[PDB]
Every structure is written in structure tokens, then in C-alpha cells.
Image: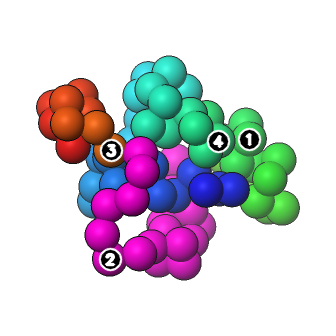
């Protein structure tokens, strides 16, 4: 859970979400909070375009994926697990 893939895939689903949930919700913040941790951590200056960073991040998003939900989703996860 060293990079914020798994919380966004296990809690939000199809692609990476917006910064109002990403900077403020634990489901995303237990990992990295946003493009500030992710541009400094990813080695590349990705944060210039949400679609381009999210695509490099989305290219990662198939690398730490087990085929089942682990520890982060809750049974009332915002609008359930």
C-alpha cells in the first residue's frame, strides 16, 4: 500500500477519483493523499494533466491488484463497501 492504487480500486472502482475525496477521505489518504505525494514519489512530472497522470497511475493500477477486497473497504464505505 506504498503507492495509492489499491484504496481507489477497492473503494471507488473504475478509474481514479477527484481530490475532494482523494485529499480528505482515509480510503485514499492511508496510501498517498494526491498528485503532490504522487509527483514527488513517481519519479516523473506527471501532475500537469489529470488524464495523463491518472493514465501513468492507471498503468500502475494493474500492478498491485489481488482479485478480492482486502482490509480498506467498510460496510458503509461512503455508499457501502
Residue 43 is situated, as x and y percent measured from the top left of the image, at 83, 61
What range is drawn magenta here? 49-72
Kindly identify which residue carries mark 2: 67
Kindly identify which residue carries mark 1: 37
Residue 2 is situated, as x and y percent measured from the top left of the image, at 69, 56
Residue 20 is situated, as x and y percent measured from the top left of the image, at 44, 23
Considering every residue shown, the one lying at the far left of the view is: 79
- Identified at 47% across, 58% down, the residue is 6
Q: Earlier in the sequence, mark 4 or mark 1?
A: 4
For marks 3 and 4, give the one nearer the viewer.
Answer: 3
Q: Which of marks 3 and 4 is nearer the N terminus?
A: 4
| Mark 2 and mark 1 residues within 8 Å of each other at the beta carbon | no
Nearer-the-camera pick, 68 or 27: 68
Residue 76 is situated, as x and y percent measured from the top left of the image, at 19, 30
For marks 4 and 1, give the one nearer the viewer.
Answer: 4
For residue 58: magenta?
Answer: yes
Q: How far apart are marks 4 and 2 (CA)?
A: 22 Å
Disc marking residue 73: 3
Q: Which of marks 4 and 2 is nearer the N terminus?
A: 4
Amino acid at each position: 500500500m506504498g503507492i495509492d492504487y489499491s484504496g481507489l480500486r477497492t473503494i471507488f472502482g473504475e478509474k481514479l477519483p477527484e481530490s475532494h475525496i482523494f485529499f480528505a477521505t482515509v480510503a485514499a489518504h492511508k496510501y498517498v493523499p494526491s498528485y503532490a505525494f504522487l509527483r514527488r514519489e513517481l519519479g516523473l512530472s506527471s501532475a500537469h494533466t489529470n488524464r495523463k497522470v491518472w493514465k501513468k497511475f492507471v498503468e500502475a493500477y494493474g500492478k498491485a491488484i489481488p482479485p478480492a477486497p482486502p482490509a480498506p473497504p467498510l460496510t458503509l464505505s461512503k455508499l457501502e463497501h
